[PDB]
Amino acid sequence: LHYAIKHKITILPLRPSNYNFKGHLKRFGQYYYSYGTYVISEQRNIITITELPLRVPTVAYIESIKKSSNRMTFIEEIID
DNA sequence: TATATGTATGTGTGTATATATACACATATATATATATA
Image 1 (spheres, rainbow, N blue to C red):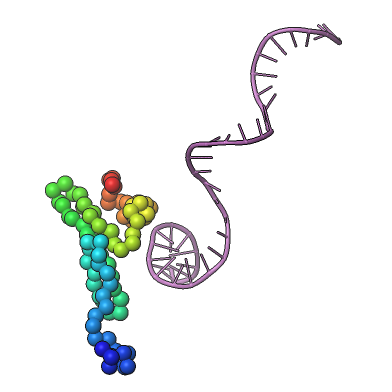
Image 2 (spheres, rainbow, N blue to C red; image 1 turned 90 degrees about the vertical axis):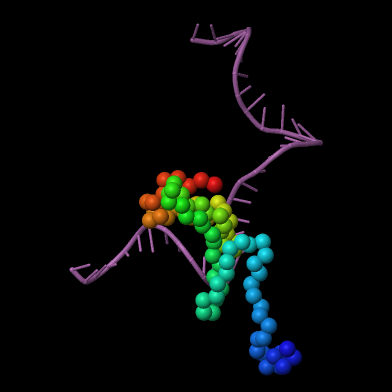
């Protein structure tokens, strides 16, 4: 590690924090991406969202999913 | 046609009760707006 401090190279990994977050994290190139969690059902055509990505408020997400007219053409009602 | 005469509003003081709003700054994302293509 002292050698790596002299030459500025990385040995031990330094990952993002996943504490108090139930979704999953992926590295695609030079960035990290954080994913939510849904639960598909065709018996009652209802998707049950169970988690949002990191630092996403809930009512701002719901109003953003309500304003977009291309997405509103497939939903009847959106309930919290 | 002037007069009263009983109506109705209306700020104002101290000590309380509960809220509201404009602006700067960076950067990533967004949802609709737009040419001209035709």
